[PDB]
Image (cartoon, rainbow, N blue to C red; front, top):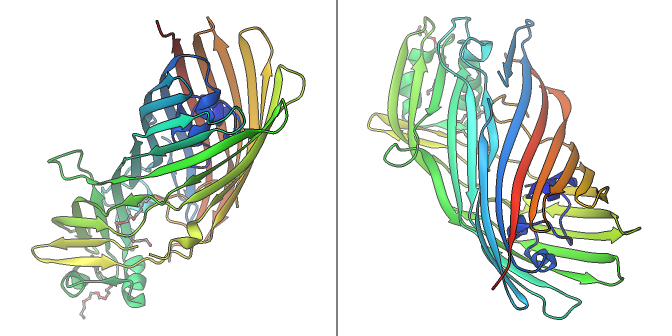
Length: 414
Ligand SMILES: CCCCCCCCOCCOCCOCCOCCO
Ligand SMILES: CCCCCCCCOCCOCCOCCOCCO
C-alpha cells in the first residue's frame, strides 16, 4: 500500500484521507468520492514500477536487478445517483519484481559451480473493489467498499547448501525430502525453488480473497477538511500452485521434482488513517496524512512443498511491528488547466529476491485537462535508496521509481 492509489494521490506523497483523489479512492478513502465533480467518472491508467537493486559478495562480485518493467492497468467507473456515488474498478499492481538473471553469484553452488538457474521474483495483486459513498449531510461523508484481491507469485530462488544447512539445523527446514536429498546436495551443492507457471491450468501460485474499507470526511472550515478510514484485514487464503524443487550436487548435477507448494499464513494487516487537507490561497492546497498499518497484529508463515517422493517444509517466523507513515502533499493551480503536485512520505534481514519496502519516497505530480471533463494526471514517486548488509555475508543497495498515469473522462447525465 503505502503511497496510496491514483496519479494524484501518489504524486502527493501518498496522501488521501480527505480530498478528491479520483476513482482510486475506492481503495483508499471512498468517502472522498463525494468531492467528485458532478456526473460520472470513467478512469483509465497505467502503473509502472522500476526497481534498482545491487547485491554484493564478500569477493566483490555483484548481481543487479533492473537489467523492462511490469505495467499494471487501472480501469474504474464512478456513478452519481443524487447524494450517492457508486463505483467499481480493477486495480492491477506489482508489489515485488526482481530479475538477477542466471550468470550471477546468486546462481552458484555453495562451492563455486555456476548453475544455470535464474534468481527472480514477481508478485502481482489485482484489486477489484465495489463501493459507494453518501453525502449524508453537507459536512460529513460516509464511504465504504469491499474488494476481491487476486494475487499471483512467481519465484525463481537458489539457496546454496550453507543456507539450507542452517535452516535444516535450525529446524526451520523439514520434511521427508530432507533425508533423501541431503546427501545429493551435500557440502558444496544447493537447492532451487521455481514457481514459473502462469495462470489457470498452468498451476501458478495464487490465491483469491476478499478485502475492504470504510471512511469519512468533514469540513470544519471553508478550506480545511479532515479525513479518516479503516481498512479490514485481507482474508486471503494460501497461495497455491505448481513448483519445481530442484536439488543440485557439488558438481552441478540437477535433480528436479515437481509438486504442490503453498505459501501459508500472510494476509495484509488492517490500517487506520488520519489526516487533513487545507487550501491557503485558492490555487494552492496542502495535505498531511498519518497512516498506521497494524502489521504487529499478524501473529498467525510457511512454505509447504509436496511431491510423490516427499516434501519439504520451511518455517520462517516474522517478527512484525506495526508501521507508521507520515505524508504531506502539495497541489498548485498554475494555469487554468495545469496543476502542479509534489510531496513526501516517511515510513518506519536480507534475501535479494524479496526486498524490504523503502523507508522514504519523494513524489511529483501534474494535471492537465483539455476540457472541464477531460483530465490527464501524472505522478512520479522515488523510493529513496537505502543501503544495508547482513557463508554469504551480503550487502544490498535498493532504490525505486514510480510512474502512474491516467486519463479521466467526466460524463454528464441526460
Ligand atoms: C531440498 C533439500 C535440501 C536438504 C539438503 C540439506 C543439505 C545440507 O547439508 C548436508 C551436508 O552433509 C553431507 C555431506 O557431503 C556428502 C559426502 O558423503 C558423505 C559420507 O562420507
Ligand atoms: C504479501 C506478500 C507475500 C509475498 C510472499 C512472497 C514471499 C514468500 O515466500 C516465498 C518462499 O517460498 C518458496 C521457497 O522456500 C523458502 C526459502 O528459504 C527462505 C530464505 O531464508
